[PDB]
Length: 143
Length: 142
Image (cartoon, rainbow over all chains, first blue to last red; front, side, top):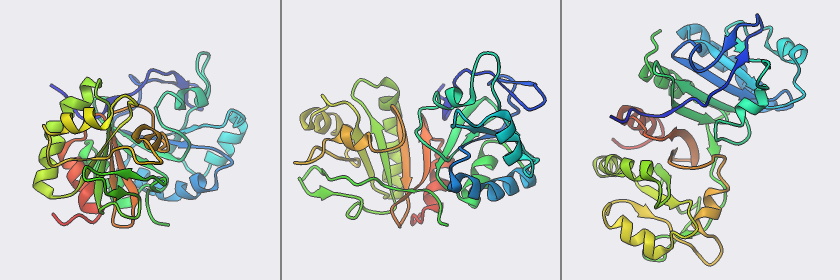
C-alpha cells in the first residue's frame, strides 16, 4: 500500500518557453536541483549534474532559491546547460517560494522524482555520480 | 570534492549513557528522525529494523518531539531492539540536534558514510533496494 518517498508539493512554474510545469506535467522520472547564483558550490556541481542529464536523457529541472535571480540572470547561467530546464515565476508562484515547500533548507539539493511523481532520493551538497545514476535507475530511468 | 554533507556537531547519549558525537558514531550508519505521534514514522520502523538486522549497520534513532523523553523513547524502542535511540545529554536534547540538520519534519532517513558524511537521504519510506544501494556506496560491509 505504501510506495517509497513523498509526493511533490503543489506548484506551478514556467519553463523559459512559457510552458507550465506542475507535479502533473513534470516529465518523469526527473531530477530537481536547487541552486542560487551566489552559491559557488551549487554552480561547481552543474557540469557533473549535466553529464548525468545527458547520458540518461532525464529532464533536470532547476530552481533558484534567490528571489533576486531574475529571468535574465537565470537564463545567462543556464545557457551552457541545454539539458537543464530552468523554472521561472508563473502568475501564481515564484521559484524561491516553491523551493521552500520541499522541507529542506539551503542549497544545493538534488531530488529524484519517480514515475509516480514521488521524491524517492535526495542528496544534500555534492551528489555522488554513481549514487545519482543508481537512484535514477531505481526510479525507472535507463542509459 | 567528496559527496554529501558533514554531520552537524552534537552530543547525545545512547541507552547505556555513553556519549555519541559525529566523531564517536559508528560508520557507516543510518540515522532516522521520528516522533512518537508520527503515524507514518512508526509504520516504517518494522522495515528499517529488518534492514538493521540483516546488514548489521547501526541505525540511530532521534525524536524531533521535545516531550519524547528517554522514558517515552526507551519504552517505545523495546519493540525495535536493534535500533540505537539517542537521548538527551547534559548539553543537547535530541530535537535540538535534529534542528541542526537541514531538513524539516519527519520521517527522514540519512545514510552516513565511513568519513561521517551524509551521502543519501530519503523522505518517508526508503525503498529497500535504494537504501541497500546507498549503504553499499557508503562503504557498508554487505
